[PDB]
Image (cartoon, rainbow over the protein chains, first blue to last red):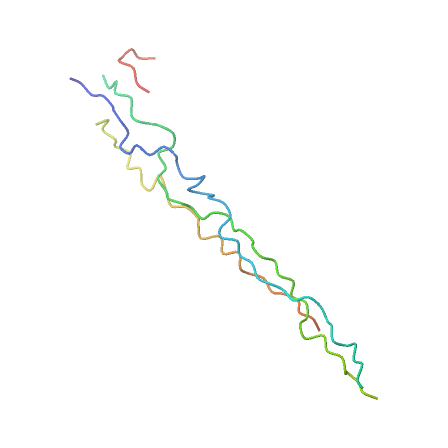
Length: 45
Length: 43
Length: 31
Length: 8
């Protein structure tokens, strides 16, 4: 039985990228925010 | 005769879970904050 | 095997996944 | 070519 090949050394195949490489955006990083500049109405007495 | 068809399925490359793109979340508006109180100037 | 004389030295080098961390950049204030 | 058992 002379030489020959066979199954891969590693089955693998997907190579590297995709859900490996670019699995997409991570947890939504967000912060709240203020609104404006009230309380200048100022109607004393 | 080597006739064994090495297992060249797809890509032999074997890295793992490369960094995915970054999401953006709650875009709060850092306006200005306080209590809208009157009395600012009693004449 | 196939008598792979060629060493294959790091034929599959690493990958540059260190890029990332989108938490950079400054920010204008209000004044 | 060089006739021999096939390979992939």
